[PDB]
Image (tube, coloured by chain):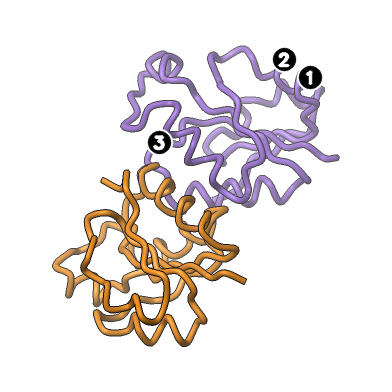
Chain colours: A orange, B purple
Amino acid sequence: MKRVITYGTYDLLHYGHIELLRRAREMGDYLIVALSTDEFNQIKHKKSYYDYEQRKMMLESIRYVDLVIPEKGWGQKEDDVEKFDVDVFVMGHDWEGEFDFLKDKCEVIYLKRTE
Amino acid sequence: MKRVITYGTYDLLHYGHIELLRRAREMGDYLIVALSTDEFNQIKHKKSYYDYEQRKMMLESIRYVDLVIPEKGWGQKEDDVEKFDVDVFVMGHDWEGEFDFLKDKCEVIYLKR
């Protein structure tokens, strides 16, 4: 089972996010989304319109989302990848290079048309 | 196959919507969503942030939604129900009584809170 993962806040979803998620899920057989908690969301210098729970509920309702886990901080990726047996790590193009350090643990992929 | 249908604009799509949709789909085996076209939105003194296509794509991505069709006007429901062999018609509480005329063609249900 090729397991894919992606991180993000996913606050006011606009079809743009759905496209990213679908493409991500498309690269495996199972997609995990590490949803930024409201505390970390704050750390990221944001104050989401929708709270974690609500954002989680919406993501879970999306056909392409198989599991939503909480992203509580910057240094949990490496651990997540191992803990959840992640095969592919996907992020938007605007993160290109930012997570290459995971390349030795899994397939790192930066999408294209991800404004 | 118990086919359910519901109408609406579903613009800035979030969980409140999801709640209604899931509940709706829950009453049958297949859920149809008649998405208000952008033209029909103006007719309802409403202007969406997301255009019909984008709203449609988002709905389609929701596990509870099996089909999205365009709602072009106020008087297509009776027709839709027949044309799509709709068994149950669902709408939010705020529409209670407003579509009872369909009761003779299908099960009309107004969700609570």
Residue drawn at (47%, 87%), measured in percent from left and top? A83
Q: Earlier in the sequence, mark 2 or mark 3?
A: 3
Residue under label 1, please give it: B82
Residue under label 2, please give it: B79
| Label pair 3/1, CB-CB below 8 angstroms | no
Q: CA distance from mark 2 to mark 1?
A: 5 Å
Residue drawn at (26%, 45%), measured in percent from left and top? A115
| Label pair 2/3, CB-CB below 8 angstroms | no
Dividing the image into 4 quarters, which one contains the N terminus of chain A?
bottom right
Q: Nearer the viewer, residue A25 or B2?
A: A25
Q: Position of residue B66 (x, y in %)?
A: 66, 40
Q: Secondary structure at mark 3?
A: loop
Q: Position of residue A106 (x, y in %)?
A: 42, 76
Q: Secondary structure at mark 2?
A: helix
Q: Nearer the viewer, residue A28 or B50?
A: A28
As drawn, B65 above or below B75: below
Q: Nearer the viewer, residue A115 or A55?
A: A115
Q: Position of residue B83 (x, y in %)?
A: 76, 18
Please identify the quarter of the rendering in which residue A113 is found.
Answer: top left
Residue under label 3, please give it: B11
Residue drawn at (39%, 71%), measured in percent from left and top? A34
Mark 2 neighbour class, 10 Å CA radius: few under 14, some 14 to 19, many 20 or more: few
User: Chain ID for label 3?
Assistant: B
Q: Earlier in the sequence, mark 3 or mark 1?
A: 3
As drawn, B37 above or below A91: above
Q: Amino acid at mark 1?
A: Glu
User: Chain ID for label 2?
Assistant: B
Residue drawn at (72%, 15%), measured in percent from left and top? B79
Mark 3 neighbour class, 10 Å CA radius: few under 14, some 14 to 19, many 20 or more: many
| Label pair 2/1, CB-CB below 8 angstroms | yes
As drawn, A98 above or below A92: below
Q: Amino acid at mark 2?
A: Asp
